[PDB]
Each structure stands twice: as structure tokens, then as C-alpha cells.
Amino acid sequence: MGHHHHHHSHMADPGREGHLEQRILQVLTEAGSPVKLAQLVKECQAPKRELNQVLYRMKKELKVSLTSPATWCLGGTDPE
């Protein structure tokens, strides 16, 4: 798994939505494939509620794309 050595951001992280976003993109990259929203909950260690609001913003920023109803994917890859 590898990523399990990371916790729920124990310290006073100066931008929780940024850290959460970095998690979502990273999970999508490790798979190299569409990751489900329900799976993004357990991986990124954040509630579906919080994920949704961030994910639509990341969609506008082309960071993520929606492949299936409640299944997300990496927006191609890192924008080179």
C-alpha cells in the first residue's frame, strides 16, 4: 500500500483542502486508473461530503475528470 505510513495530517496543516487534494490526485496516479468516490473516502481519510465540494473545484482546474456517476479519475496526468 505504501501510503498507509501517512496519517490523517496530525499537525496544524496550513490548507487542509490542499493536502486532501494532493491525496486525491496521488491515489488516482498510484492506480493509474479511475478511483471510486467511496474508495476516495477511505484512501484520502476524508468524508464524502468534503471530497465532493473539493472534487468539483479540481474538475474546474482539470485536475480530475468524472468517468462514471460516483467514480473519479486523474485529469489525464500531471499537466506538463
Image (tube, rainbow, N blue to C red):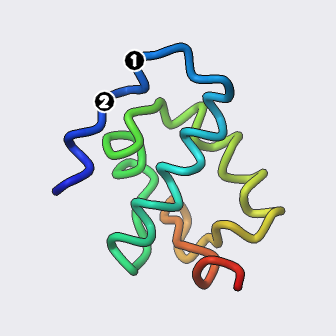
**Residue 53 figure quarter:** top right
Identified at 38% across, 48% down, the residue is 38
Quadrant of the drawing holding the C terminus? bottom right
* Side of 16 where 1 appears, left or right: left
Q: Are marks 2 and 1 in contact (CB under 8 Å)?
A: yes
Expressed as whole percent of the image width and height from the top left, the position of residue 79 reads 70, 80
Q: Which residue is mark 2?
A: 7
State how far apart marks 2 and 1 are (Cα): 7 Å
* Side of 55 where 47 appears, left or right: left
The front one of 40 and 27 is: 27
Q: SS of the residue at dot 2? A: loop
> Please, which residue is most extreme toward the right here?
60
The front one of 31 and 3 is: 3
Q: Is residue 10 above or below residue 32?
A: above
Q: Please tell me how crowded label 2 is: few (under 14), some (14-19), or many (20+) other residues with Cα within 10 Å.
A: few
**Residue 5 figure quarter:** top left
Q: SS of the residue at dot 1? A: loop
Check residue 10 in the rendering and tell me which mark sits there, or answer none: 1
Disc 1 residue type (three-letter): His
Disc 2 residue type (three-letter): His
Expressed as whole percent of the image width and height from the top left, the position of residue 45 reads 38, 34
Q: Please tell me how crowded label 1 is: few (under 14), some (14-19), or many (20+) other residues with Cα within 10 Å.
A: few
Quadrant of the drawing holding the N terminus? bottom left
Expressed as whole percent of the image width and height from the top left, the position of residue 21 reads 59, 48
Identified at 63% across, 43% down, the residue is 52
